[PDB]
Length: 130
Image 1 (cartoon, helix red, strand yellow):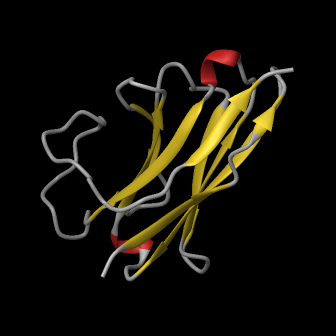
Image 2 (cartoon, rainbow, N blue to C red):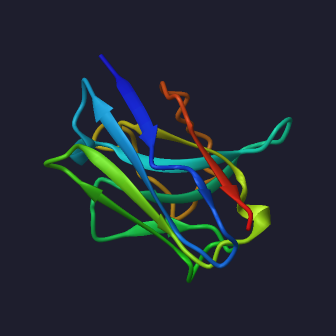
């Protein structure tokens, strides 16, 4: 069984900050790798930030490096995404998804490998406006 829930998205002013939560059930996050994904109306998905089976290393987009920060909690079974220095262009619905990293072959140092997620989710709405 696999289920996930995105939370913590809302309205915020430009120059503000936000804190998202990707909670999970039926599986334990320690054995998986989790990524956060944007979606605007009719647009493709942006890979924002991600965390592997090893909590000591993480991925980030060049548009968010130095203002976004990801971390996980294996007692809460949740991945948290902090964001800061927010612009109107950051407005989107934020989704999350997992991959069975303690089971797949070697993950590259990138978010554009031929393997993909496609797990369950609901998304959480983020708007940046004064």
